[PDB]
Image (cartoon, rainbow, N blue to C red):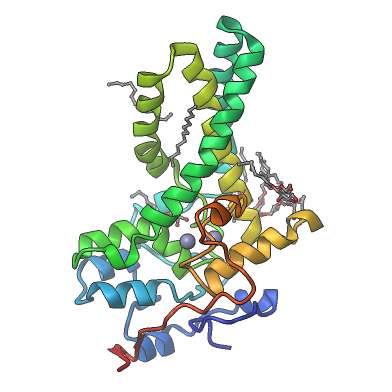
Length: 274
Ligand SMILES: CCCCCCCCO[C@@H]1O[C@H](CO)[C@@H](O)[C@H](O)[C@H]1O
Ligand SMILES: CCCCCCCCO[C@@H]1O[C@H](CO)[C@@H](O)[C@H](O)[C@H]1O
Ligand SMILES: CCCCCCCCO[C@@H]1O[C@H](CO)[C@@H](O)[C@H](O)[C@H]1O
Ligand SMILES: CCCCCCCCO[C@@H]1O[C@H](CO)[C@@H](O)[C@H](O)[C@H]1O
Ligand SMILES: CCCCCCCCO[C@@H]1O[C@H](CO)[C@@H](O)[C@H](O)[C@H]1O
Ligand SMILES: CCCCCCCCO[C@@H]1O[C@H](CO)[C@@H](O)[C@H](O)[C@H]1O
Ligand SMILES: CCCCCCCCCCCCC
Ligand SMILES: CCCCCCCCCCCCC
Ligand SMILES: [Zn+2]
Ligand SMILES: [Zn+2]
């Protein structure tokens, strides 16, 4: 019924594309007006941190279109289709791996590629849990809330916005750059080519996976990974940080089991309970 309320069990697929009534939603929760560009609305807010984090993770839906972040001529940068990630980055994967395969034992290059993929899944778990869901640990700053929003908050705010799910290359480059330098500073040159190629390939698998978890009836073997990730959205976002798998969830005890609690809804009509 109301999308802002977490559920113990996921509802129907088509209840997740029900457009939010903008006026009602603003008046009811006193948060963001979906009808107006969201970013300045955050930059110039009187939110305190606990309210922002409580509210941004209670999902809404703009409808068939995409909510405005800027509303001006910068708006194209905020829209990135699923196919953008493979076309942008798979050529980089193939170039770095191809280099390694001409200057190094190919069998060890393949092996170092695979450990790149393995390290990616750990990064995937770590970024998601500790950077993306900084949440409670956030300052009392609007610039912090806007940064959070841009990195992951928006996606929790609007799960079914098909153009605000995968990472825009502009942001990806900023995050990837320190990893690229670190790998090429530690590892022997052509080991870095093979290793980085793998980590990068793992990233592409992640975001594509992440996309199709939201916007697709998947083949059966992935169908339960879909339930798992969607529960991270509509049940508990303190758990279920793995999205290509719950491997690292199990390892670090953040698995999202079938009697996991709901997440707290601290605020209502602008005010906190108790
Ligand atoms: C100012 C440069 C344009 C910013 C576009 C804002 C759209 C934010 O896009 C976000 O990218 C994050 C990772 O980068 C992803 O984790 C989120 O799922 C996605 O919402
Ligand atoms: C990796 C190369 C991919 C080739 C392009 C795939 C065809 C794109 O297909 C697009 O999919 C969109 C899904 O959001 C639809 O909204 C568009 O109508 C459709 O044209
Ligand atoms: C590495 C890339 C793996 C992903 C390829 C999956 C291709 C899915 O196929 C696409 O699904 C889209 C759903 O958004 C539809 O809009 C497109 O019409 C369809 O071509
Ligand atoms: C590698 C190039 C693949 C191009 C993918 C085609 C998708 C973009 O083309 C169009 O973009 C429009 C945006 O308004 C969408 O509304 C359409 O559904 C889509 O087909
Ligand atoms: C980052 C891209 C690679 C992901 C690595 C982890 C993928 C694990 O994937 C899982 O493997 C299981 C095997 O027991 C299968 O049962 C599941 O269907 C599959 O989702
Ligand atoms: C790492 C890659 C993860 C994505 C793989 C699963 C994507 C499944 O995507 C599938 O694409 C099909 C072809 O158009 C569509 O018919 C299906 O509706 C869609 O589920
Ligand atoms: C492909 C991921 C982004 C790569 C960023 C490269 C950072 C610069 C590398 C060379 C260092 C110049 C000072
Ligand atoms: C053996 C070292 C592997 C290093 C892999 C680095 C992965 C780069 C992708 C980083 C993505 C940041 C979001
Ligand atoms: Zn998601
Ligand atoms: Zn999340």
